Amino acid sequence: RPTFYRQELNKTIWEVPERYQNLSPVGGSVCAAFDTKTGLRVAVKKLSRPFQSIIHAKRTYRELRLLKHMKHENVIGLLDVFTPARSLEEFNDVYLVTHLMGADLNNIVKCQKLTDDHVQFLIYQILRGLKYIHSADIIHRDLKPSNLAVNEDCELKILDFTRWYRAPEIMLNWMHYNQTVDIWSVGCIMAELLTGRTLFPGTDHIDQLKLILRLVGTPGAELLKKISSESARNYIQSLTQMPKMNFANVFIGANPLAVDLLEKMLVLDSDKRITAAQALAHAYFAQYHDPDDEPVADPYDQSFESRDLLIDEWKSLTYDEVISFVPPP
Ligand SMILES: CCCCCCCCO[C@@H]1O[C@H](CO)[C@@H](O)[C@H](O)[C@H]1O
């Protein structure tokens, strides 16, 4: 058990292994810090109201279990996790420590116009991390430029687990989402890397859906066939019957292989969207693809997801997970 010290940043207290120094707010609350032990800049995150309700307590546990399991180059991982509390009885606060990646993809696209080679590599690393996430049977569900950290070498990590990058079926609360909701996201992000502009900058919920329909067109008979509801099913007919656009004509001048990949991500029907593993074999990534260096995750026990427990059950399990934590090499 290390030594802790106390300090107030903005309007909140932090107690941290003394090895963590120069705490400075960045936006639970987050602080950048220097890891005196390893010599590297870190992010330390203090979980808001970890055990306030049953839902929060389950979310805390989910969050830790998830991040504990993420061991991949293109996915954020845990350097450390600590509480100031000795014993479960005292246990009330949880801190997570990860790499301070010092620029995100939004920051990169605003300033620099990226080449074809840049977008192959960036999207390639997204799909690579994504293949690993999906192979644990997890859906990210919030991929966007600000959830993607990028260094000087234009190397990328997925952060996470606005609506411009959200699959239309989440916006319609369709339920049982499949993993290709993240693929939709990747398609929006890639369109934006290619053009420098947000593909679907909706002002609100319906606007979002409006701009989507103008690009990819109103649902095809094959898709309408799958819409359980007389409800949803009409209104659609009643809409200005839009043509699916030619992506060739929208992303004019882009690599035609990139344009083909985009048609395969930005399909309305989630059943027809390319998967992360299939996209990695797409000819667009021929320069970067290596079928032996695109690993999948260990099996992720998420049976907890289906259980309804008492707050103290959730916290104790969270405590076990703090105690069980082994740092990476
Ligand atoms: C905005 C107009 C309608 C949007 C159509 C979105 C269709 C998304 O695709 C749907 O994904 C579901 C998973 O949610 C699958 O069960 C369906 O089989 C599939 O068609």
Image (cartoon, rainbow, N blue to C red):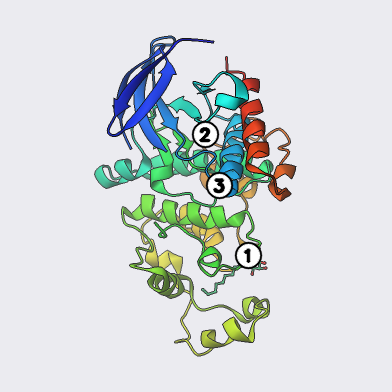
Going from N to C along the chain, the mark reached first, 3 or 2, is 3
- Identify residue type, mark 3: Ser
Tell me which amino acid carries mark 1.
Met
Q: Which residue is mark 1?
A: 175
Q: Amino acid at mark 2?
A: Asn
Q: Looking at the picture, how far across and down is residue 186, in whole percent?
A: 49, 51
The secondary structure type at the circle numbered 1 is: loop
* Residue 219 on image: x %, y %: 56, 78
Q: Taking 38 as reference, is 233 left or right?
A: right
> Which circle's residue, 2 or 1, is located before the other in the chain?
2
Instruction: Tell me which label, 3 or 1, sits earlier in the chain.
Output: 3
Tell which of 310 and 317 is nearer to you: 310
Whether residue 39 can be seen here: yes
Label disc, if present, on residue 74 of the rendered structure? 2
Residue at 39% across / 40% down in the picture?
118
Say which quarter of the image contains residue 28: top left
| Crowd around label 2: few <14 · some 14–19 · many ≥20 (10 Å) | many
Q: Is residue 65 above or below residue 55?
A: above
Secondary structure state at the residue bearing disc 3: loop
Q: Quadrant of residue 104?
A: top left
